[PDB]
Structures are given as structure tokens and as C-alpha cells.
Amino acid sequence: KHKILHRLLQDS
Amino acid sequence: KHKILHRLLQD
Amino acid sequence: SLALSLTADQMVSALLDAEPPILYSEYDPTRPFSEASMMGLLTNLADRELVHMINWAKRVPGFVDLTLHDQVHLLECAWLEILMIGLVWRSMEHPGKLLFAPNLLLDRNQGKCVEGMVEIFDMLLATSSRFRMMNLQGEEFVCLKSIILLNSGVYTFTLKSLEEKDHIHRVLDKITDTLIHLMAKAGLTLQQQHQRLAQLLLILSHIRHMSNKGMEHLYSMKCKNVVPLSDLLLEMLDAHRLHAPT
Amino acid sequence: KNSLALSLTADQMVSALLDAEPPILYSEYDPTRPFSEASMMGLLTNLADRELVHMINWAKRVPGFVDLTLHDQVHLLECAWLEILMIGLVWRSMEHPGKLLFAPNLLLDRNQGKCVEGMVEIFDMLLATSSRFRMMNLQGEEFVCLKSIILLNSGVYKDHIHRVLDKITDTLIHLMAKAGLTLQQQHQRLAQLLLILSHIRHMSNKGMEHLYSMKCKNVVPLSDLLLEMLDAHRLHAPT
Ligand SMILES: O=S(=O)(OC1C=CCC=C1)[C@@H]1C[C@@H]2O[C@H]1C(c1ccc(O)cc1)=C2c1ccc(O)cc1
Ligand SMILES: O=S(=O)(OC1C=CCC=C1)[C@@H]1C[C@@H]2O[C@H]1C(c1ccc(O)cc1)=C2c1ccc(O)cc1
């Protein structure tokens, strides 16, 4: 499980 | 409030 | 690698283009102020700013060269310092006030609405006054904000993890070269350049202090339950609450 | 009236700072190799209390400091004391990788930081700062300049302090130029050193927050001086 910040940073 | 620092800083 | 190949002028152009927009608050002057409503406006504003900050960080040269876990760590550590430097920058031309948004200009007296907030407002106003008297330039501001992002979490991070820190230090050296280039272009003598470089970096310690003092009030139970906080902001706050005393 | 500090030359500034250095104090020999919350806090508080007396007399000898009002002198020391103790600790820990030399007879590793709740994280940050100073080959003359900058820069906002801070900058640049560094190397090293100051501020804020909590205050009896230095920061803390 990865946090909102990790998710938004990951996004492309 | 009389601080210790006030005393210690005096010569 | 792309960060190291940039000339100082290219570094400035890339940082200027990466700049996030100025957002509006939901401030309504027909409504009176309270602790809850003031906390509500600032949290909602900070929350929408975080999303633009995440996308700004990705455009900071050398930032995407880091691992995802390191990008998360730097943003968790620096987010409030970054919001604060942006606030003191846009507040420069408003002596005695903080321009939170084009529609939200607040005095130190309005800071007394929230318990423990006026002390922070005084520090933010002092910093804004210091930037004004130094005639801080937009080009310098973008360099400082980038230094905050890259520097604030660099020491709180195997040999693989050590290469990440070395790369951060190289990019920070590039931002210093950029700051000096800007000052030299501005006609400052070498003594003036070094003195200005130093004055700007010392201001960064004040911004760290303000963020730590502010963060401590934000993750206290009173401020966490004053208004319903958003999920991303809660996680960003918890990254700090986690190390705080029980 | 005009301050003597500004009339000082770079060499006279360095020599005034090196001469003002407080000594390295010893821990009490009584408890050896601390492994409890009480023994660890007992040794560190006793040591910090003794170093504070030396710090006050050191600050009086920092050019420009005596020219401030007594009220401003109190404010700067209240703001900077833990940052000053921490930069001192990190400096003397340099030649001891992975260890914190609190005193020549008190060398502690990170496992000892675990004995006090909330301490190991600060210990880790201190070790990484000592390690950074080691890799940069921080010199004694640079250290005394950084320590004086911490004292004068502690208070978030002024003319006199900013003129003294500029003189210290000139002194740091004078030392690096004397060491053979080029102009690019001088500005790069000046920036590296001052950015470490943001980290020393962060460690102080994080440590202070634990030190002024009730649980930290109750572990061992604290001297009246230490309690007054803590309460200067506790006053701004949330309720
Ligand atoms: O450090 S603070 O003053 O936070 C508090 C809050 C309560 C009591 C004491 C300090 C902070 C700086 C400024 O006012 C606060 C605050 C804030 C940030 C995040 C939140 O979740 C809520 C509020 C501020 C701020 C908000 C947006 C900006 O672009 C810049 C600063
Ligand atoms: O920030 S700290 O790690 O403090 C704590 C204490 C308990 C829990 C978390 C942090 C602090 C730095 C170093 O270890 C602590 C501590 C200390 C200082 C004053 C006190 O009244 C008590 C302890 C430290 C220290 C003591 C003397 C020095 O010369 C340098 C550092």
C-alpha cells in the first residue's frame, strides 16, 4: 500500500 | 519574572 | 544528469517555467472571522496548493532523478517550508500583511483568531520584511524554493542510498552557482555576492524554524479536530506527527 | 554607538573566536555506559547544565554580542542554546564515525539513543551531520564562525546583527581563500556550510519539542537554569 503523495508523484 | 540568564549575562 | 548539464541561465528559465499558479481562497468578507473558519480557509488553501507543489517538484531539475521513496521523503519534510516561502514572497509588497491569496490579505491581528498562530504570523511578517529590504528577485526566490525542497530532507534519509545524497549535493552546488550568477549579472561586487548568498541561506534556517513551530501546532489534537482536515494534508502532517512526543 | 566587531580584521575575528572557545567538559565518571532512560537523561542534563555556564561566558566574548542590549542577549541565547550544544557535539564527534562524543569519557552510539523515547531519531540526525562535516573536512576556524552565526542568527526577526553576520561571512570567505580554494569553490563551500545550519536548526526544534514535554521534564530533576532555557521555547508550544 502506497500513500496519496506516492501515488501523485508516481502519476504520468 | 527574574531570569537566571539575566544575572549570568551581567559582568 | 540533465540538472548538471544546465547552464545557470537554463536553470533559472526551467525554475521560472515550473512555477505553480497563485490560488484563491474561499474567503467571504461578508462572513465574520473565527478560529474554525480561519483554520478552514487556510487548510483548504494549503490542500489545493499541495497538489500544484507535487507537480512543481517534478519539474525541479534533478528531482525526478531520485527514487520515488526519496521524492516522497523530501516533500514530506519540506512542504510547509515551501508554502511559507511562497507566502512570504507574495507578501513582500504588502507591509504588515500576509497575502495568503489575492482575495485573502491578513494582518497580525487576524492571526490572533487561532491559538498559537500570531507568533508564527509575526515570524512570517519579519521574513517578508527581510525579503523586501533585500529587494529579493523572482529569479533568486525560485532558486531558494528549490534549495528548500532538495536540502530539507537530505540528512534524515546501503551504498545505493548514498549515491542519492551525492546527486542532491551536486544539484544544490548547481543552484548556488545559479544564485551567484544572478548576483554577478546584477552588478554586485564579489564581496556583495558572498554576503547576499549568505544572507539568503541564513533566512532558510528561519524558514525551517517557522515550519517546525507551525507543524507542531498543526499536528496538535486541537488543530487536527478544529476543522475536518483533508486526507493528503493529514498524511503530510503525520509524516511529522510520527516523530513528535506522545 | 559603533561596535568594535566591525573594525576587527578577518584574522582578528578568527583569533577572537578561537580564543573564546569554551573547554571540552567531562561527564561525571560515577555512572558508566548508560542503558536506562534515567541514567542517559541524568548524564546529558548534568553535562548540558555545566556547558551552559561556559556558553554564556563564550557568547559575551563573540564580537558584536556585548553591543546588544541585555534583553537581546537573553533572547539570542534562549533561541540558540540547543543548536550551539549540538554543533559543538557534532564537531567533537567528527573523528569518531558512527559515535557521538558527548564528552571524552562519554562516547555514545545510536543503540544508547534507544534508551530514551524519541532520542534515537535525533541521534541519527546528529551522526549524519557529524559525518557530513567530516567528509567536508570542516576546519576549526570555520567551526567557530558557524557557531557564532548560529548565536546571532537564532532569533527570527536588526541592523547591527546583520552587519556582524556580514563580517562573519567575509571571515569564512577569507579562510577558504587562505586555504587555496577558487572563487567557485569558495561560494560552493560557503553555501554547503550554511545549508547545514538549516539542519542544525531542525535538530534543535525536534529535540527541544521532546525536552520540554512533561514526560521528558519528569525523568530526572532539572537545574533551575536548564528549566528556564526550556520554558523560553515551551511558551510558544501548543496547549
Ligand atoms: O504555521 S502556521 O501559522 O500554522 C499554525 C496553525 C495554528 C496555530 C499555529 C500555527 C501556518 C502558516 C500559515 O498559517 C498556517 C498555514 C496553514 C498551512 C497548512 C494547514 O494545514 C493549515 C494552515 C499557513 C499557510 C497556508 C498556505 C500557504 O500558502 C502558506 C501558509
Ligand atoms: O535533542 S536531544 O536528543 O534531546 C532529546 C531528549 C529526549 C528525547 C528526545 C530528544 C538532545 C541532543 C543531545 O541528546 C539530547 C541532549 C540533551 C541536552 C539538554 C538536555 O536538557 C537534555 C539532553 C543532547 C546534548 C547534550 C549536551 C551536548 O553538549 C550536546 C547535546
Image (spheres, coloured by chain):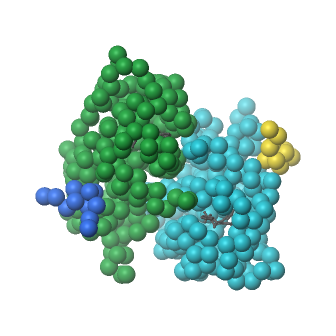
Chain colours: A blue, B yellow, C green, D cyan
Q: Is C164 placed left or right of C213 in the picture?
A: left
Residue at 63% of width from left, 37% of height from top?
A: D160
- Percent position of residue C186, x then y: 35, 39
- Percent position of residue D16, x then y: 72, 56
Q: Quadrant of ligand 1?
A: top left
Q: Is D169 placed left or right of C13 in the picture?
A: right
- Percent position of residue D35, x then y: 67, 80
**Quick one: C199 or D168, which is closer to the camera?**
C199
Residue at 72% of width from left, 75% of height from top?
A: D39
Quadrant of the drawing holding the C terminus of chain D: top right
Residue furthest to the top: C30
* Location of residue C206 with respect to D160 vertically, above or below: below
Visible in this render: residue D51? Answer: no
**Quick one: C185 or C226, which is closer to the camera?**
C226
Quadrant of the drawing holding the N terminus of chain D: top right
Q: Is D223 placed left or right of C24 in the picture?
A: right
Q: Quadrant of residue D219?
A: bottom right
Residue at 73% of width from left, 43% of height from top?
A: D74
Visible in this render: residue C109? Answer: yes
- Percent position of residue C135, x then y: 41, 33
